[PDB]
Length: 189
Length: 189
Image (cartoon, rainbow over all chains, first blue to last red; front, side, top):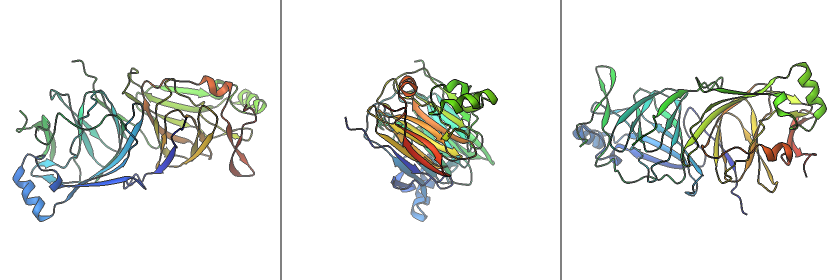
């Protein structure tokens, strides 16, 4: 049979860049509906429209058994009181796991079951997080430097319904009085 | 529903040690039959019998779509002219990818299809390697310090060590006149 060609690629742990990867940039204007304080979001778009995160994906063709990987630079910031985050993956094939790996910065992972029972895991350099089957997840930057991480998902997991852009997550992550706080999301029904 | 608990663990990128992950120690005496030079293997066993490599492993119950992960401290050394390696596996379920991430040290990967065609990939820090479906593989240390790395594989890939001592890999990796060389395995048939 014709076997796939194996390869090695370099990754900078200080910049998350992979040479040759499929780059993708998400600005704040690409995240309408996602943050709670919708007016802060408007003010911050017109006046800067900052970069929220960069992804560097190395994805295969979507077969059972095969693996994709991805680095993300998630930049620091706030939209109101709420911390910058990724859009949030919820899988098409639900019982896939994912392994995330912290490379540089301070952050964490917001997780939730389909019904919205929530879990928060802190992430410093070196922390490897196992996302189990059936869990949604989104990564948040809770520090002052870019949070960079490597992600390893199955090729056949996908991203769709259970949508985050209209529905979202049971809890949000915010800064109250210097301190980090996982609290309830008022927009979650 | 019954859902699995997500978690974080802490991986030291300077030492390989995952906290509370449970070690496997393979000392030279556990790799009988693996290195071309059987007689240098006996000699080096009698005298010292060192730990060739350690594995700190976080596994799930094997279940299509779940992932394990594990670091390896592959210690440095040689058996005659041939550098120290992992025993290396074909998977029990063959069409399964892995992804490796090199953390410290200097090394490489040896890879091979069921029919024998080899492939060598340099690994230094930053090197992520995609091990595609249907390939066996073995990690090799080629410098004077430990080669430490992380691996993420499908939880149900299983473990075929049998084809690899019995038959071998088609190519071995040795030091010859100071420079690292990848050559044919005299054992190979």
